[PDB]
Length: 208
Length: 142
Image (tube, rainbow over all chains, first blue to last red):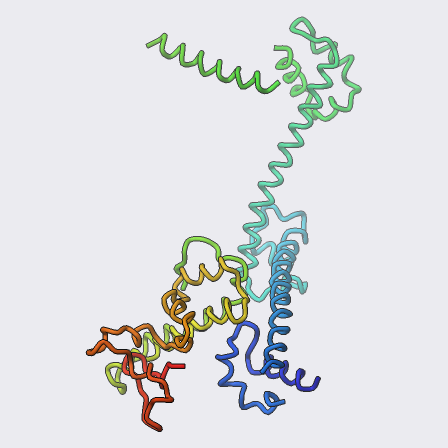
């Protein structure tokens, strides 16, 4: 057991690891008295190699998590810092150890920029999806009444106002415009697009 | 080597990247080494060795340690870190400790032979100085 401990100490003390050749560190470790203390060395090296192959992936995951934590510190230490510049996000978040763990500050700026762009895209997409869901709910609530071109928005306001779906539309003018649009399943839609192509080609060729 | 194949390296790259960076630094330092004070051919000696050492590093990670994936090994091959021909020669029997490809190129020598370092120490003169001219090795035989 002491021989194995000495072998591990020699492997970790002379600037060696699982990413340095044994036949390249043999000229730097053979003189160690602990080296003298075939197959046991090979077995220990293999076990250390496997353990360190797991541990290096773990350390890379730890570094990725540290980058994510630096991004979270730069983004969630204030009111989401949407348009806060590097100086603004630095003067308010230069004390905690989450940012102090990052040895490079340029990495912090690059991560902040990339994460801010990704978060802006994600927020825009989420807002658009919520708006689509609200529009679908409003259209479904408006379709609950037998409305046509003769139907007026005054009766829709008197019979569909209490519906929570109509409450999703925060503007009355927008609701009226949606009602007017609505007043004036997919393979057949594909044939409809084919027909659209046919009619557009027909009008073009007929004009020519 | 900042100049790469316009992509991201395969998984397991960061494990071996610092050692390759150190070898790249050594190679660059060897390139810029002034050639005054040495002979004409000795200035080329380090590169070979570094190249050999470099090609050892990947070759000791895919066969004797199995520490890298196949795709990572081919990425190292394609980026100039590993030498495909030298590795192919090493797979043979009796060519495990081959220093450089030039020492076995038959017709590079005047008589269609190998380098002097290819001669095994068993049938070599006892105590002779063995200094190769192509790469400067003490005998790359078995």
